[PDB]
DNA sequence: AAAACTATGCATGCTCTACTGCTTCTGATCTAGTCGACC
């Protein structure tokens, strides 16, 4: 689950553990935020979202199911 | 011609400085195992 306020991002797991270190707390750093920051529309500054985090292979353009690996 | 003084060489001990071999300490590497958290 992702919390967004302006340029500030925060991520939480199923049981409540912080994961912002991995996914980035600002567009300058991270593994997802620098690329998803510009996806949001002009009028949206505060947001809470819930979803799944997955691994994507661009070569085959396919989701790699995280059975137990990668 | 005989006796006293001195020079030089050599033996002797002790002290000091390189080289080889044994023992111990450190670093580097690999292998095995543990823990967080997800599902």
Image (tube, rainbow, N blue to C red):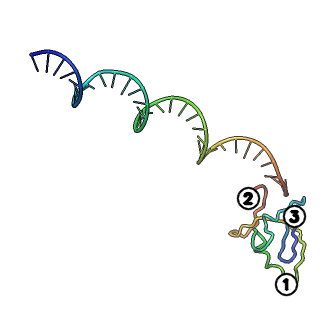
Real-space CA distance between mark 1 and mark 3, rounded to the nearest whole angstrom: 25 Å
Q: Nearer the viewer, residue B36 or A61?
A: B36
For the residues beneath circles 1 and 3, the answer to whether they share a chain is yes
| Residue B25, quarter of the rendered image | top right
Name the spot of residue A5 as percent of width and height, x first: 87, 75
For the residues beneath circles 3 and 2, the answer to whether they share a chain is yes
Specify the subunit that label 2 lies on: A
- First along the sequence among labels 3 and 2: 3
Mark 3: few, some, or many residues within 10 Å (few <14, many ≥20)?
some
Specify the subunit that label 1 lies on: A
Under circle 1, the secondary element is: loop
Name the spot of residue B39 as percent of width and height, x first: 85, 57
Q: Which mark is residue A42?
A: 1
Q: Nearer the viewer, residue B4 or A68?
A: B4
Residue under the image location 84 percent in, 82 percent down: A41
Under circle 3, the secondary element is: loop
Residue under the image location 85 percent in, 84 percent down: A42
Up-down relation of residue A7 to residue A20 (above or below): below
Real-space CA distance between mark 3 and mark 2, rounded to the nearest whole angstrom: 21 Å
Q: Which mark is residue A70?
A: 2
For the residues beneath circles 2 and 1, the answer to whether they share a chain is yes
Specify the subunit that label 3 lies on: A
- First along the sequence among labels 1 and 3: 3
Mark 1: few, some, or many residues within 10 Å (few <14, many ≥20)?
few
Up-down relation of residue A69 to residue A57 (above or below): above
Screen quadrant of the N terminus of chain A: bottom right
Q: Which mark is residue A12?
A: 3
Up-down relation of residue A27 to residue A53 (above or below): below
| Residue B9, quarter of the rendered image | top left
Residue under the image location 90 percent in, 58 percent down: A15
């Amino acid at each position: 689950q992702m919390h967004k306020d302006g340029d500030v991002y925060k991520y939480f797991s199923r049981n409540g553990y912080n994961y912002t270190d991995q996914f980035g707390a600002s567009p300058t750093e991270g593994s997802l935020t620098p690329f998803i920051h510009n996806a949001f529309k002009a009028d949206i500054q505060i947001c809470i979202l819930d979803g799944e985090m997955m691994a994507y292979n661009p070569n085959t353009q396919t989701f790699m199911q995280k059975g137990t690996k990668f």
